[PDB]
Amino acid sequence: GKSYPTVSADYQKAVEKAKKKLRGFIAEKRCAPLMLRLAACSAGTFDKGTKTGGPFGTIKHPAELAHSANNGLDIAVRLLEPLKAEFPILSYADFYQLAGVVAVEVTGGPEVPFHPGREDKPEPPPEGRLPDATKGSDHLRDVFGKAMGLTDQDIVALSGGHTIGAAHKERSGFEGPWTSNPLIFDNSYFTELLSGEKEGLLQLPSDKALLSDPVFRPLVDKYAADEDAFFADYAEAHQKLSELGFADA
Amino acid sequence: GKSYPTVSADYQKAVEKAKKKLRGFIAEKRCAPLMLRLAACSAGTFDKGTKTGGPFGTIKHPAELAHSANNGLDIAVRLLEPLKAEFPILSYADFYQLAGVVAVEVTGGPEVPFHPGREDKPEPPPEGRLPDATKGSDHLRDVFGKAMGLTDQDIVALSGGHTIGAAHKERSGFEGPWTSNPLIFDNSYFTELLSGEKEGLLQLPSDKALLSDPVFRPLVDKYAADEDAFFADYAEAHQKLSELGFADA
Ligand code: HEM
Ligand code: HEM
Ligand SMILES: [K+]
Ligand SMILES: [K+]
Image (cartoon, rainbow over all chains, first blue to last red):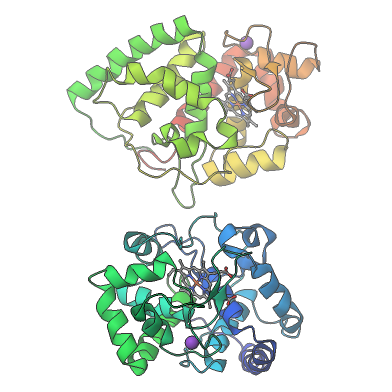
């Protein structure tokens, strides 16, 4: 259902150059998980009914950075600003989604397709649309399904984004990595979720919700057994998330 | 641009009976200004672009009552609940707008036309759509015009709703009546606004903004000189406000 806009050759050349610069920067700075979180938090505010929010550059605004679910994302924005300044032709919206795609690639994940053309919008969405880590399956469906318009498959695959990174007690309050290799994009999130709590590792109530739901659980099992299947479904879901409200809602 | 819904004869009979009961109750309780504020605060959250918010009964929800601009409105809702219970067939949305229309009538104001059929909606709008008393004309146009879809004339006439009632230092922080006769609906709001600050009386910065704007000021002058003209424009504006998002946005 997507009809992608035309951008100039110069715009396309900037996308390609920025992609390379983002690879080197993100790898050197060890900030792939923070950048994936920035991209997801940016996109996840989309509401299909009103066609408001979504990946349109608003996360750089102090008002959106101040949302409790976005604690620490001011660091991500600050980290990217010098590189963004080398690409004035690119929208912030495109730049942040490109950073998210690169974060997945540089950690060894799938190559998520990227299409340019998002425009920077003036007004941030209201606070409270991002998912609550303390809630369960009904809540996940309210946020990813009723608001964003994504599928149950997308919910499980995207939850696998937690295969990289960690929570911080000073940000959310939760603490620690989901996996033993938090800079490696693999299916270990699902294998750890299945094996139960392990010292040093994290499971949010929202992660655990996937285990007890009749639709989510078979997907968790599938992804734990088959990393290729996880990668395929992940790439599909990340692309959709990154394009919410864009080139047709 | 309105196409009003059909309601049953029993619904119409309840509207008429509730109107009478609201007259007696509001007059006896001396709460007309509080009820006019309840109706206006309910309706003023409408956003024409997204077709969200508006006079759809959500003001009774704890979450909307908790909005800072709605301080004290929990009292208004509590006051009306026993009477509302005598009319189970009526929507809360209709009931609160009817209370606002009656508040104006019983204090001697114009007879604002009323059409039933608003449905009670499940979700309150986000906080922050109601006007800020410390701001000026640009802000008033953003809220009443860009969001609600009302005219400059409507802004000045509706500001005259302050001809009844008072601010409270424990609610907004502002304090006192706009007029010497705060239970009498007349054009004195405009005459006091023009005459400058008077001890015992209140002018918000948002009221004062009407004085210096090239479009608003001639209307203030007109209403101060001609109460009949004020009543006509007020009735038109109140009707529009009470029907935002209803029977065609
Ligand atoms: C499914 C609902 C989700 C919930 C409830 C949730 C919640 C959280 C929480 C509480 C944190 C910890 C923040 C901190 O304390 O630093 C976090 C981190 C993170 N999230 Fe999610 N999230 C969800 C979905 C997603 C999605 C869809 C993605 C991307 C596909 C994602 C990517 C990440 C990453 C990469 C981190 C680590 C950040 C870092 O290492 O600094 N999350 N998430
Ligand atoms: C134009 C932008 C407006 C602003 C900035 C504004 C602001 C305020 C504030 C700060 C208060 C004091 C609340 C308190 O401390 O108790 C108040 C009270 C009140 N407002 Fe407005 N208001 C506006 C428009 C309206 C409109 C359109 C109406 C109805 C037509 C209205 C009707 C009232 C009434 C009747 C009161 C008195 C409530 C009482 O006596 O308890 N206002 N308003
Ligand atoms: K991992
Ligand atoms: K008066």
